[PDB]
Every structure is written in structure tokens, then in C-alpha cells.
Image (cartoon, rainbow over all chains, first blue to last red; front, side, top):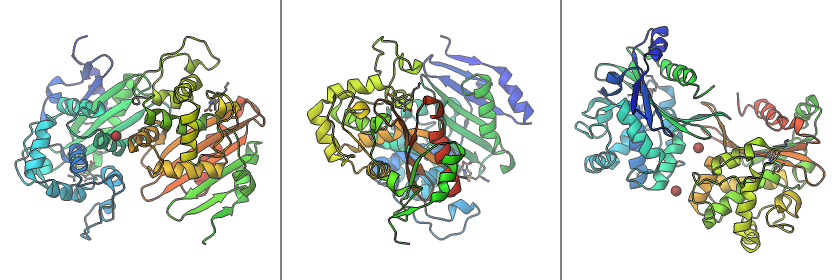
Length: 244
Length: 245
Ligand SMILES: C[C@@H](O)[C@@H](C(=O)O)[C@H]1C[C@H](SCCNC=N)C(C(=O)O)=N1
Ligand SMILES: C[C@@H](O)[C@@H](C(=O)O)[C@H]1C[C@H](SCCNC=N)C(C(=O)O)=N1
Ligand SMILES: [Br-]
Ligand SMILES: [Br-]
């Protein structure tokens, strides 16, 4: 029944990939947490695109996003991610981490409502200091891997202070992978604007009889290693027999 | 092309490869065009069997017979032939493992009058619930074709059925079968064995970034040995049509 255990054997997966970072797991049935690094599990970083989870919730709950079908027209400014230079709905904007769509949401939400909602969500340090459309990229907001798990457990249980409908739509938008053995609902992030540059993957694995929450971050000096966010998480999930 | 339904007999090669007979129906939502290997069998009506778990789930949720997708339905303690049925279930695992006994209990609590009204409102197949209120989708009067399954699924996809948006969102969650970075499949299997001819079903849709492809297939299923062919043949057609890589 001991709340948090360190499992340093997971460091072998970081070392194999010449990488540094943390994986945090939470067994919902047992109410027990596991991590390779208790210190880094509680270190706070810019959320970057993992902020698209609360941003989606707030946009839906305020009617900035009507539903997951509403089209957000490309503003016609060519950016260096090809998938961003096109129309999106909530599903594809989350999938392709389409920053400019979410910047527009944030502008329409505005500072007062963004701040109130992140306090109601107990989200990270709850600090939106900076620009309302970029604070999750280079403003004051910080969140640890353990704080990501706390937030995700509320979302999973529809316990956040927004409608059940808003929570159901965001959980649909988080869908990443599914088969006959598991479902992954998750969101990637890449924080580059303030050091240290890190990759995120946060979400959960739905099994028939349990839910395993996860939050990982890792040093990401270049975009070359971004695939390691999922690969290292899956190495840990497989070692723990959570997925085959 | 303007044609509602187009016949593509090349898909019969996927049936023949597996010494099988049946139909695949596809509907391109963007183009409002349908495709099938067999226009006649596409419109032949059969017992829905476990594909009936889609409307049954919707009606159970809408009436409050099922509170949500977490509510536990305790095993009645009767050992049945399918191991996965002999345990507690929620809506997600009851759909996944086609747990008939749970859905029979839903049907009893919904009752004949409300079941009949709802299937009329859904324009579901021949709308006929004659037989036992807790088995009519297995051995009663209800019949539905592959094209009628697509018509019903399009209403569900668009939240247009006459039940709450919430009921429709929960059932679409319960239908989740497969997802990756290229596509999402929401679907339901069926195996009709109580009245001849014995057939297998797979009905649902493929969500892409920019389109939805609805599908409904059935095939002759004399034994449970071939049940894997429902998904395998459908995927061979989806690949041929470049819907999935
Ligand atoms: C701040 C954004 O740039 C960043 C974020 O918000 O986290 C975007 C960029 C990439 S999508 C392609 C990744 N390649 C980046 N060089 C991404 C992600 O992997 O989640 N999010
Ligand atoms: C038998 C029917 O109740 C059937 C139905 O209601 O459609 C059940 C069992 C089969 S899978 C198991 C088939 N037999 C295996 N030995 C099934 C399905 O494939 O969805 N549902
Ligand atoms: Br809802
Ligand atoms: Br889903």
C-alpha cells in the first residue's frame, strides 16, 4: 500500500537510448505510483503541447470550440510543420499539435478565464504570467510529471470543474492507440523556448480491469529523439507487463 | 460519378482466397457514394445478433438502465460456454466480449413497448421485435441488411438518433476497436447461430483525418473457426480501396 516506489531498473531503457529522463506510472486500482527517479518526477517544466489538454477543456466549456467537428481555417501563414498549413478540427489539431489553432483558442479564452480555470483544475503552478497565447511555451506555467498524473486522474473520472461533455470530447481527442489489449489516450509535447529542452508524453493506458496513468519527460536537445518519448514509455510498460 | 451504389466484384477475390461467401459494403461520407462486391446481398436482411448491442446500449443508456460506462454488471453465477462471459462486466468490456447475458438483462428492463418505440424512432432494419424481449435479435423477427446497418451508423456518427448526445458519445466510445496514427475503427462484431443461415457480421466505420468510411460486412459462418475472417476480409477491402495503408 506504499504510495511511491522508485524502480531504478527503468534507467536501463534511458541508457540503451543514450537519454536522460523520468517515467512516472500510477496503478489506479492499487493507488500506487512507480518512477525511475523520484526527484525528476517532481521537477516542474513548461507543459508545451501537453497544455493542449486543459486548453481544449476550457475552449469547449466556454463555447470557443462548439464540438470536435468545427473547422479552424488555416490563417494562410506558412509554418515549418507541413501538417499545420491546413484546416483542422479539435481531433486533428490535437493529433498534429497545431500550436496556431490553440493560440487562437487562448486569445478568445483570455487571461481572466484561463487563470480561473487553471486554479479550478489545480493545474501545475497555476501561473499564466506572460502572453495569453504563448505562456505554456515561454511564460510562467510549470508542471511536474506527478502533477500531470494528478490532473489526468481528475479528467479520467470526469472530476474537473467543466461539463462531463467537455471531458468526454477531450478524452476522445486524446485517443492515440488502441487494439484488443489496450487503449492509450495521451498527448505529446516538446518544450524548446527555455532550457532544458524536454520531450513529454502524458496520458493513460486503459485495460479491461485497470487504468495505468503515465507521465514521462526526457532531455530533448534536438527533434531527432522525439520518437524516444513513446519508445521509452512502451519499454517500461512492457517490462511491467502492462502491455504485451 | 453521381451513382448511389457501385458494384466492385474484384473484392470477391478476398472471399474466395478464404473459401468464403459474403458482402462488404463501404460508404464514403465526403462523396456520399457507396461500394459493394454484391448489390443483392448488400440489401439482404439477416438477424443482427451482437450488432444489436449498438442500439441496445443506446436505449439502455438513454432510459438510465445503464448509468454510465463504469457501472458493473455482476455475473449471475451461471457458467456459460464463452469464458469471458463468466465474470463482472461494464459497458466497455460487455461490448468488447459481446456479453449476451448482460444485454438480455438490459432488454428485460427496457421492455417490449419502449424497445419497439425506439427501433421505430431509429428506422432500424424491419423494426420488428416479435419473439422474446430478451432474445429477439438472436431468434426473433428483427432483420437488417448491410446497407441498413450503414444508414443506422451514419445517424449514430452524426449524433442524429433520437436519444441524448451523451448516450451516442458513450456507445461510440464503447465501439472503439482499433486506433493508430493513420485511422480509428469503431465497430461491433456479430455471429448469428440460432436461425439458418449462420452468418458473421462486422459493422462500423473508419475515421480518417479528412473523411469517414462506413462499413458493413456479413459472411456465411457455418462454424466459429472462421470468425477472424470478418475483420481480415474487411481489412483486405479497406487496403485495396486505399482507405488504410
Ligand atoms: C512548442 C511546439 O513547437 C511543440 C509543443 O507545443 O510541444 C509542438 C511541436 C511538436 S510537433 C513536431 C515536432 N517537431 C518539433 N521540432 C510537438 C509535439 O511533439 O507535441 N508539439
Ligand atoms: C453466439 C451469439 O450469442 C453471438 C452474438 O450474440 O452475436 C455472440 C458470440 C459471438 S463470438 C463466440 C461464438 N462461439 C464461439 N464458440 C459474438 C460476436 O462475434 O460478437 N457474439
Ligand atoms: Br456527456
Ligand atoms: Br474513443
